[PDB]
Image (cartoon, rainbow, N blue to C red; front, side):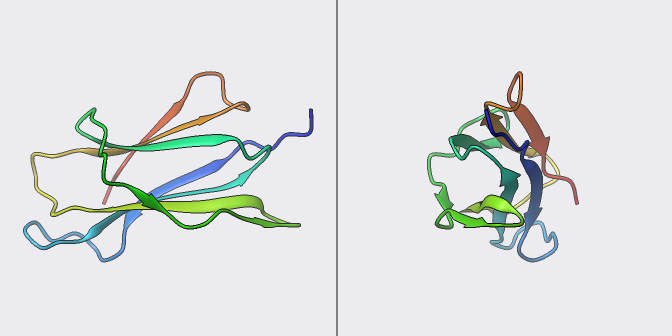
Amino acid sequence: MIQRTPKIQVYSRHPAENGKSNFLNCYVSGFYPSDIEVDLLKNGERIEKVEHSDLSFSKDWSFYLLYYTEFTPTEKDEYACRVNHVTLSQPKIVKWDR
């Protein structure tokens, strides 16, 4: 089948400041086909408030879209992008760094 393994990148809009509302961002790109599943994990858990760009597609990048959610950071918390895609054996988990 025609296929392209997604690039995943996780990050926030504005750099980290531990009591101020920010957004958490998972940018998934370069994938084909375009059946994809992306979840943001707040401490191995499943932020049920999560939105995404419309899904776009370019002759060069192929398929790409962004998932974000609002989130006042902390030293405790750890945040992650789970991505599943046909190209990937098991789902990839990408942890929000800084």
